[PDB]
Image (cartoon, rainbow over all chains, first blue to last red; front, side, top):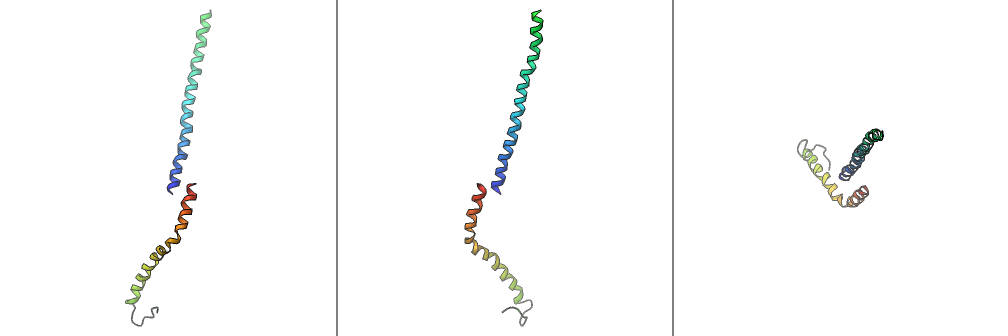
Length: 48
Length: 48
């Protein structure tokens, strides 16, 4: 029973690890897209 | 001999339950050396 409860900690470690990495992965990706749309209006008015 | 109540009815037949009650858990301990092989098989398979 001690091997079973110890093995359940490894299972819960990976389940949390999949979520925690995916949260910050989506946040950093979104920041690159957000600033990109702002730069389009900056370049457009500059050309006129 | 077994009780047939010829000299007893609270005398010997009371302590009969206590002598047999002491004998039974101690028998499992004596047989415990046969349970040593079962121990090596049990925790090794679960760990894998």
